[PDB]
Image (tube, helix red, strand yellow):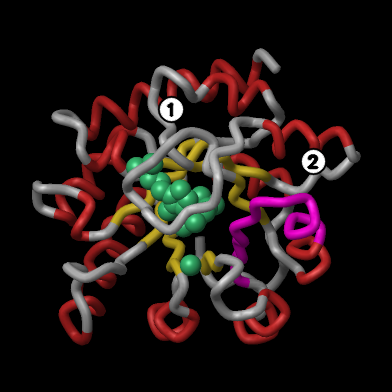
Amino acid sequence: HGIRMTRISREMMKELLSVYFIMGSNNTKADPVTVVQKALKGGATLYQFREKGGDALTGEARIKFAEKAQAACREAGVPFIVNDDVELALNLKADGIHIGQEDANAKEVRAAIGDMILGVAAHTMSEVKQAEEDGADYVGLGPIYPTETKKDTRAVQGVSLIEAVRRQGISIPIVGIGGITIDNAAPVIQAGADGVSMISAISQAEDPESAARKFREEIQTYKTGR
Ligand SMILES: Cc1ncsc1CCOP(=O)(O)O
Ligand SMILES: C=C1C=NC(C(F)(F)F)=NC1=N
Ligand SMILES: [Mg+2]
């Protein structure tokens, strides 16, 4: 995964979304980079650097942590996505950036990042359609299930939006997020999603490598079976 000179294909994007691990230093009691390394070894197909909150790293310490996480992704051959921070994504030559409804406007971000991967968090049909129009390569829909990892989230929606989007003929790459575990991931894929994203199911697992491997194995099975 080098510098992109063309927009990523939908086929490739959907493959990358399979097991999308997201993490910040304040999401685990273990060593942050070590957990990321274990998740990648287990089978995570994409990683998002999400460092925010009161006890998250800032300044130079945050940048250095990001560099080490990006290096871990490079060693595993997995793309590195930055959450919220467009400047950081450009400065590190990240593979992509993820933004939400309260962040920089998607039109503005797409113009600033060229052909880098762009993900947009959506909670309604209107937002999903707007994201596609603005040039997003994928949308993150949720929260599917209850979650305490992110407090300022909108109402839990199950797989309702995923189903509605596919029903309207929209084929944009979709990843589900919010309280997803190895036990409840199947319905997300069966509803039409191209993958599942998670923080705590892997970051707080007593065995992150095994947890990631389990996710990878079952998601592959579900995608072939739906
Ligand atoms: C970042 C984010 N965005 C919507 S829900 C969520 C949290 C996912 O965390 P967990 O997988 O631990 O529920
Ligand atoms: C709020 C979010 C929603 N979706 C995603 C992703 F999984 F990447 F799509 N990441 C986020 N940080
Ligand atoms: Mg955001």
- Checking the image for residue 225, the label placed there is none
> In the shown orientation, is residue 85 left or right of residue 205?
right
- N-terminal-most mark, 2 or 1: 2
In whole angstroms, how far apart are the C-alphas of marks 2 and 1? 24 Å
Verify whether residue 119 appears in magenta.
Answer: yes
Verify whether residue 77 appears in magenta.
Answer: no
Give the tally of numbered discs: 2
Q: Residue 225: x, y in percent? A: 66, 13
- Residue range in magenta is 116-129
Which image quadrant is residue 226 in? top right
Q: Is residue 153 above or below residue 116?
A: above
Q: Residue 158: x, y in percent? A: 59, 31
Which residue, as the protein is rendered here, is positioned at the far right? 169
Q: Residue 51: x, y in percent? A: 30, 67
Q: Residue at x 34, y 26 (%)?
A: 213
Which residue corresponds to mark 1?
216
Q: Is residue 78 at least partly visible in the picture?
A: no
Judge: label 2 CB < 8 Å from ligand 2: no
Which residue corresponds to mark 2?
165
> In the shown orientation, is residue 95 left or right of residue 119?
left
> In the shown orientation, is residue 207 left or right of residue 76?
left
